[PDB]
RNA sequence: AAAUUGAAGAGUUUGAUCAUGGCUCAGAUUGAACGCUGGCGGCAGGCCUAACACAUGCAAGUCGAACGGUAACAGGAAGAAGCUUGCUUCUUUGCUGACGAGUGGCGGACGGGUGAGUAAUGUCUGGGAAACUGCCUGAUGGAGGGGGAUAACUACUGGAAACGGUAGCUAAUACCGCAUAACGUCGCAAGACCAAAGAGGGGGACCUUCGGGCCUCUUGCCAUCGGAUGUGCCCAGAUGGGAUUAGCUAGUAGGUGGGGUAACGGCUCACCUAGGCGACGAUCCCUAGCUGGUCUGAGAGGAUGACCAGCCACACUGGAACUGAGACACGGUCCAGACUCCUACGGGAGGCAGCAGUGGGGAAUAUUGCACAAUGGGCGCAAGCCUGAUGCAGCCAUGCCGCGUGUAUGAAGAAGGCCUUCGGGUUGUAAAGUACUUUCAGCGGGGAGGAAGGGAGUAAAGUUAAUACCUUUGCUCAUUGACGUUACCCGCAGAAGAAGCACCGGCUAACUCCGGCCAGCAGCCCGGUAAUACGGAGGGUGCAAGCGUUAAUCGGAAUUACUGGGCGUAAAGCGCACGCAGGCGGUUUGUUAAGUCAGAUGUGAAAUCCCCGGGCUCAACCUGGGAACUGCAUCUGAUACUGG
């Protein structure tokens, strides 16, 4: 129910950085990003339509660390909700608890953010929530527990996040080690190199 | 004011009873065509007033025999 | 029977069967008397048998042996049959 | 006779009773005549867990319907709170 | 406010093309099975086949406030003491707390199981009249006075047993008359007729024949008319296939009369009439429980009817009735049959398609568990007893959902493995090393909620002649949990206990090396000596506590085309015509309002589906409200079109 193997292999296969490493270096200094994994990585074959759709879906999944059953249920709920299916899907993906904890700055990677959440080190409205897929609603307050504020993991993650960009829908205080989920991000707030319509066409065929 | 039916008498050979055929116009449940459907009822005809072909008005009552549960109200058109 | 209540119910049921059989045979005899008086055409004997039959029929209908509807049926039938003679 | 009782719906270890008017011979969760409320015994006191209509309940009690002991206690507490 | 916002193609006939046409695939889904593998939890599901046969335990009892009672244990008791005189230990007493057996009342027709039969004696929808209805409930009345028995018991006695027989005794709210008798039954009427039962709590005095009568309250009893509920009955429409089944029917169709039922009725009988059903499929044959619903589909449809809920049928096979308000009765009765068992050989006993379980069949489906603590049920004034319903637990990855099997750093990129143009590349930050963390599992400590009640006390009110008893209402006290070591929380230790399956020629994401049309693969179109198709290795791809294969349904399949196809040559115009039933029908006026349309009412069970919220740490799941249930009937109108 988790991917534990090599991380940079996924970003090499997707041809794009998936932020699977903290950021102490550039990925170019740790692996051949422009080369696909394996013995036959130098070749690049012409992808089919199904190939491109599958590769975009896998890129999104590996970005958010979501397996196929949960992602299929996410698409089902997004197609159930009113509006455009793609932005609904991306909003449902961004609402996760481990995703927010990573974006909040308490995790260097979404894997260590998921470890922080699962290990009962993250609180939501004063209630310790240890579900990574926990849907965070607007106005929710996310904070590190008193016992886990002493970890150097959170400090390094805070620093690494300060060297990153700041999301518009997160009001975080690094001193109190707490943040607020103000609102769900609109389509224009997430990455622009993610084609949601490819996933919609892949799941609607 | 009482709920009733209307049909034509197709048989009066029995005594005190007639067989009235209630024809109805029903749309076919699949192909949408309006088809004719016939409902033949054993009706109690006391006084033997109805002949073959009369357009009669009948109503439902208690069972009067093994197959008769409807009774006559009046005759509208009389076999001509 | 396997249950104790089933055995006691069987005993009580056969006892009540015998009691009800005696009562029903009495009532049937007293009604057959009226029917035979009807057959004979004797209206005085018919009314006498009807007057003897009515109370026990009402009593067995009240004691739960037969229904009040059955008692009323017997009374009405025999009355209408007596009135067809005199 | 006709009785007003609870039908234990809900999940395992989290019961949810529906106050139903039913003929006392049917099963608990079986055939009933009319549902006149509900009762959530594990309510968080933040929400409502007692919404049993007293109008139809009184109408049925006026027709000889019997009230079970739990429904009688529920009616008493609903009258006291309201 | 929301609650139809919904529709994808590909491979394969040919040297090639277009069309036709079938086969196959990509999607969902399952009561699944098998193979490899397998950490935890929540919620659900779990004999689809042999309605095959069943060992064993339990699944329906309850009331002493109906009754005679006392056999058992607990007490009171009068009288006799071992005697270590305050332990008193046995002789007799229903005196009472209770209670075995027995009569009696209620319940065993509910609850639970299965889908054999049933193609309409059923189910669904919508109507109806000729009916009954225990317990619950409203109103009005009555509740008087007697008798004969009988179980238990006693004595004798027959049987291996099962179970009886005879004689005597006793009780009742058991049974039977009498009186009474109407807004009840019969009858137009006069009149005639029909019922009952007590028990319990307490008590001021008056009167007691020392049991108590007398007062009050509760409860029970009988009669009638209603309510509610349940059930019985009738009609219309709908509800599989076959014409290689076209005629069927003698109680058959109807009528009069007798009987019968709670009730209408050929329900039954006598007689009379000669009918009735059928091409709109009667009759016959095969299959089949029906529905809300479930799966699939854009929809229309197709398939289906496990769990949950309603209805029906069945209870070893066939038949039958008895009791009862209700049965022709799973754990009742009688008979017959098959089978199994006990036997003293004369006779007996039994029916898991109740809960576990066994043998068998099968590819395949679980424990001979805990508790009545909650809900419901039976009985009881109540306490309470019973409850394999039910609440839980055990087993199974069977499904859905959630979480974990670590995280960060980590190179000239170690070793080995594989490939190599022998330069190197890849496995690969992957590992090792370093720093950190401890969800879940393991050990220990705290700890909700499911719990409402019930009991004992007092106080108030009502009732009453009564400041008793009883009912209701406040408060006080001591308690009520199978789950259970609960959920949840806290502490400890250590990466420590936790990743596999399928695939890589195209469809279809994923490529190289090595070993001869053989071995083998294959869902549809490879292998005859450098095979991306066989087998192994490296690498990669997709899923992931699962992964594949098989079986099955729908989709794609517009491939049964109503929505939505065709027939010159691809499958398809009868050889031609006349013509009954049927289908359709020029044009105008009037009328009707059957089709059609509009509005309203009733109904369309709950659950499920969908929408907005709520509670479980999230989800699954549970749940509030709404929408929906596209249908049917009735009533009132419209008159353009179809019909008369």
Image: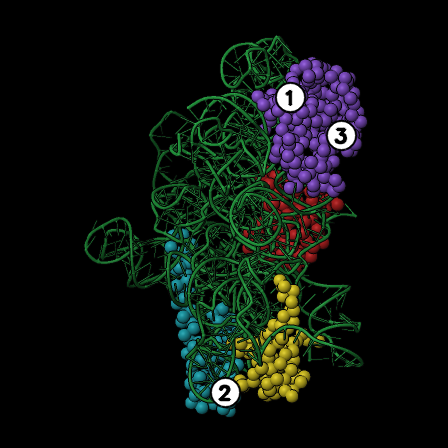
Chain colours: A purple, B yellow, C cyan, D red, E green
Q: Which residue is mark 1?
A: A35
* Same subunit: marks 2 and 3: no
Q: Is residue D4 visible?
A: yes
Q: CA distance from mark 1 to mark 3?
A: 23 Å
Q: Residue at x 51, y 89 (%)?
A: C84
Which quadrant of the figure contains the N terminus of chain C? bottom left
Q: Nearer the viewer, residue E10 or E260?
A: E10
Query: In the structure shown, which secondary structural element does the residue marked by tag 1 occupy?
Result: loop
Query: In the structure shown, which secondary structural element does the residue marked by tag 3 occupy?
Result: loop
> Contact (CB < 8 A) between labels 1 and 3?
no
Q: Which residue is mark 2?
A: C82
Q: CA distance from mark 2 to mark 3?
A: 107 Å
Q: Quadrant of residue E230?
A: bottom right
Q: Position of residue E483 (x, y in %)?
A: 53, 34
Judge the density around disc 1: few (<14), some (14-19), many (≥20) Cα neighbours within 10 Å.
Answer: some
Relative horizontal placement of residue E296, taking residue C24 as reference (left or right):
right
Q: CA distance from mark 2 to mark 1?
A: 117 Å
In this view, the mark in front (1 or 3): 1
Q: Nearer the viewer, residue D43 or E183?
A: D43
Disc 1 or 3, which lies upstream in sequence?
A: 1
Q: Is residue E215 above or below residue E456?
A: below
Q: Is residue A59 above or below residue D77?
A: above
Q: Is residue A33 above or below residue E75?
A: above
Q: Residue at x 63, y 54 (%)?
A: D21
Q: Which residue is mark 3?
A: A192
Q: Residue at x 50, y 87 (%)?
A: C82
Judge the density around disc 2: few (<14), some (14-19), many (≥20) Cα neighbours within 10 Å.
Answer: many
Query: In the structure shown, which secondary structural element does the residue marked by tag 2 occupy?
Result: helix
Q: Position of residue E366 (x, y in %)?
A: 44, 39
Q: Is residue A54 visible?
A: no
In this view, the mark in front (2 or 1): 1
Protein chain holding label 3: A
């Amino acid at each position: 129910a988790r991917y534990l193997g090599p991380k940079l292999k996924l970003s090499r296969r997707e041809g794009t950085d998936l932020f699977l490493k903290s950021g102490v270096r550039a990925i170019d200094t740790k692996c051949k990003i422009e080369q696909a994994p394996g013995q036959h990585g130098a070749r690049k074959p012409r992808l089919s339509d199904y190939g491109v759709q599958l590769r975009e879906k896998q890129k999104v999944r590996r970005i958010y660390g979501v397996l196929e059953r949960q992602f299929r249920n996410y698409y089902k709920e997004a197609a159930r909700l009113k509006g455009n299916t793609g932005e609904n899907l991306l909003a449902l993906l961004e609402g996760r608890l481990d995703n927010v904890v990573y974006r909040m700055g308490f995790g260097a990677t979404r894997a260590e953010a998921r470890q922080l959440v699962s290990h009962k080190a993250i609180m939501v409205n004063g209630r310790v929530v240890n579900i990574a897929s926990y849907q965070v609603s607007p106005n929710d307050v996310v904070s590190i527990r008193e016992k886990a504020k002493k970890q150097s993991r959170v400090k390094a993650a805070l620093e690494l996040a300060e060297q990153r960009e700041k999301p518009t829908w997160l009001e975080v205080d690094a001193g109190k080690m707490e943040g607020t989920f103000k609102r769900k991000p609109e389509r224009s707030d997430l990455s622009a190199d993610i084609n949601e319509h490819l996933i919609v066409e892949l799941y609607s065929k | 004011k009482i709920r009733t039916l209307q049909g034509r008498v197709v048989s009066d050979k029995m005594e005190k009873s007639i067989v009235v055929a209630i024809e109805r116009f029903v749309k076919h449940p699949i192909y949408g065509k309006f088809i004719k459907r016939t409902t033949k009822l054993h009706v109690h005809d006391e006084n033997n007033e109805c002949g073959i072909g009369d357009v009669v008005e009948i109503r439902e009552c208690r069972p009067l025999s093994k197959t008769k549960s409807w009774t006559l109200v009046r005759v509208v058109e009389k076999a001509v | 029977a396997n249950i104790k209540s089933a055995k006691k119910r069987a005993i009580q049921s056969e006892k009540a069967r015998k009691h009800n059989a005696s009562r029903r045979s009495m009532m049937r005899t007293f009604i057959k008397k009226v029917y035979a008086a009807i057959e004979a055409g004797d209206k005085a004997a018919a009314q006498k048998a009807f007057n003897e039959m009515q109370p026990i029929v009402d009593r067995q209908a009240a004691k739960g042996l037969i229904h009040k509807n059955k008692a009323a049926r017997h009374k009405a039938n025999l009355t209408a049959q007596i009135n067809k003679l005199a | 006779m006709v009785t007003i009782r609870l039908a234990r719906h809900g999940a395992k270890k989290r019961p949810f009773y529906q106050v139903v008017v039913a003929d006392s011979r049917n099963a608990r969760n079986g055939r009933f005549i009319e549902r006149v409320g509900f009762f959530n015994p594990i309510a968080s006191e933040k929400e409502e867990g007692t919404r049993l209509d007293l109008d139809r309940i009184a109408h049925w009690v006026g027709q000889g319907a019997t009230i079970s002991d739990r429904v009688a206690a529920l009616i008493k507490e609903v009258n006291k709170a309201a």
